[PDB]
Amino acid sequence: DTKEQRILRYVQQNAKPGDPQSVLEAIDTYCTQKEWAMNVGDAKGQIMDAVIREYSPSLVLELGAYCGYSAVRMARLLQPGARLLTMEMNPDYAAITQQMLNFAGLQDKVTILNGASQDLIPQLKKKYDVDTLDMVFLDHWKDRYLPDTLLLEKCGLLRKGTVLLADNVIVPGTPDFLAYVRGSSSFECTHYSSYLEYMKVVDGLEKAIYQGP
Ligand SMILES: CCNc1ncnc2c1ncn2[C@@H]1O[C@H](/C=C/CNC(=O)c2cc(-c3ccc(F)cc3)cc(O)c2O)[C@@H](O)[C@H]1O
Ligand SMILES: [Cl-]
Ligand SMILES: [Cl-]
Ligand SMILES: [Mg+2]
């Protein structure tokens, strides 16, 4: 029995079916009162909410679903017709994410893609009929933010005004990612200082808006 299974079970027993906000609240309560887990959390979540509301993206890609917290958080704020694609390499977590989305009633807005980002990203145009992405949320292995950003560019999946939003740029940190988006004339960057999920360690998100090549 895993921590991730316990979190799902807690949501299933306590949250309100088909109520995404109640699902987020139940996850936050579990992590506040029981076991910590690497969800973006409430504090950084408020920033994520503001970005989704501001830019109203039609197609979002999330890298790293884990238990589905960020998928629920983003999908609940998408406009009618808008869609989220979330990539997750670990099939146990992909199964948990699907059950979370099902409970939240968000399953028709979200598609879980099984596998590693480096293998799925190059298939998005052909296999999954994507032209370009409006937003990308990065929250997977921290040394893969830079390589995947470069792969997204190479594959032609970013357009002028595509918003990249990256978690954990301070803790654990994504220093190479930051040096790249901040140094590159291809991105205009904003830093959002906040706190690591479920504690008071300073962490932040970076918003990097693609400008074209
Ligand atoms: C191989 C790269 N491509 C990938 N493609 C698809 N899914 C991927 C990928 N990498 C990782 N994943 C999945 O993303 C998730 C992993 C995320 C990594 N997150 C962290 O390490 C993380 C870690 C912390 C943290 C912070 C402070 C600490 F003291 C200890 C840990 C905080 C966070 O908010 C984090 O996001 C898992 O579900 C994993 O299976
Ligand atoms: Cl929090
Ligand atoms: Cl736009
Ligand atoms: Mg994170």
Image (cartoon, rainbow, N blue to C red):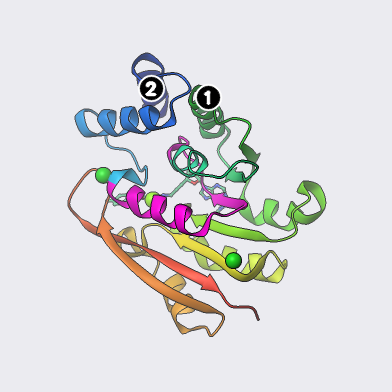
Q: Residue at x 53, y 25 (%)?
A: 105
Q: CA distance from mark 1 to mark 2?
A: 10 Å
Is 198 on the left or on the right of 58, as rendered? Answer: left
Please identify the quadrant where the C terminus is shown: bottom right
- Farthest residue to the right: give it: 126
Q: Residue at x 36, y 47 (%)?
A: 40
Residue bearing the label numbered 2: 11
Name the spot of residue 170 as percent of width and height, x first.
31, 64
Residue bearing the label numbered 1: 99
Q: Is residue 68 magenta?
A: yes
Q: Residue at x 59, y 30 (%)?
A: 107
Is 43 on the left or on the right of 39, as rendered? Answer: left
Marking on residue 186: none
Name the spot of residue 116 as percent of width and height, x first.
62, 49
Does residue 19 appear in the picture of this structure? yes
Q: What range of the chain is rendered magenta?
A: 43-69
Amino acid type assigned to the residue bearing label 2 in the image: Val
Mark 2: give few (<14), some (14-19) or many (20+) Cα within 10 Å.
many
Classify mark 1: helix, strand or loop: helix
